[PDB]
Image (cartoon, rainbow, N blue to C red; front, side):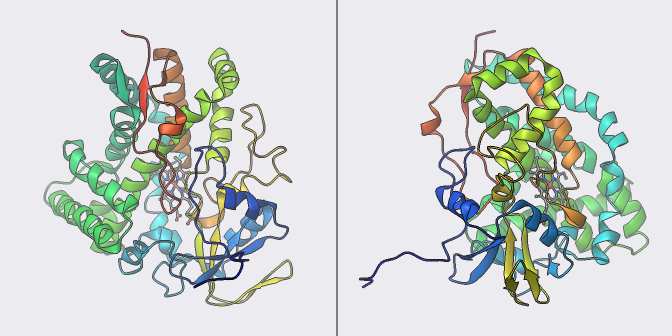
Length: 406
Ligand code: HEM
């Protein structure tokens, strides 16, 4: 057996959070090591680079030599479940320019600033509606299943034209796909969603439909500008991202804010602080911190280190968002700080399409919780919560909460 010291200079990656709003111990070590890159070992033994510093993360996310093609054999897989993505058709998150832009531009009209503004009444109505139901249904609740997940789910379904009557099916399928640990169950969940979306496309070809899927069917698909399979992949990407990211931000923001009651109280006293607090929570919680997988298609020199063609690179935006040369005392939550330039949404051509919808949802949600349930508190200690592993979007699958009755 192994009878020698076990220290490595390529630690296992990813690591799991033990506290919802702090770096895993291994990530703090990576943050502290000088230099933009560090070697890591992925689940299957293959070595990869992680980017651990803020400016280098921007530079490398902007470098066209780091491809987003998940079907490349050398793309960095962080769990066996990734092989489902490598073997499946790709939405534009997995495309490089110029193909990336031709698909992304088919969807941007739904996510413009003007459109996001017009969505405020629907978002406020959805948030307060689910709040009405939860506040009436019990002294305690699971904030995730009763509030954090249904709210962004209903909103993105309206944007897409996906009927919410099927929400039990596709919410469950979304969860299985994002949170699966093995390739078979990820593949089944993708096929479940794909078959559902394919039937919706045929329905819209018979009776033109609402929302973005309706528009893609009536226009780009009818002109042959997007393949049917690509339309499915695109709708699936938007559906899942629209569900899972905002829901995780909501639950983790509640946990984090209740552990910083002085800042939560200041926020309640001055709602002009809510947009800045949302930016700080995005920086601090960085829930998609592994969404920056890339593969080099050519050699890239980075500050004396060399990324060789064919190596995998993961831009770890949670670590980059704790760069003390950008955010003073980076491990402190400070809703009054400038969290500008954070990487929670990435950077460059793939920067999050939904970022301003997410910012709107989280502002409405925080204002609604402070308005309607100012007495909200966790029903279990933080040490009893179960955090998702570092191989998926960060969050908690259950969040027991209570408040003052009626
Ligand atoms: C709530 C917090 C959210 C976070 C932290 C987040 C995070 C991210 C990140 C880091 C990326 C970059 C991926 C990469 O570089 O490979 C990304 C891309 C993307 N996100 Fe978000 N996201 C959020 C919400 C949303 C929402 C609500 C939607 C709604 C559809 C969405 C849709 C997308 C899409 C379509 C892309 C791919 C963009 C492209 O490849 O051009 N996201 N997201």
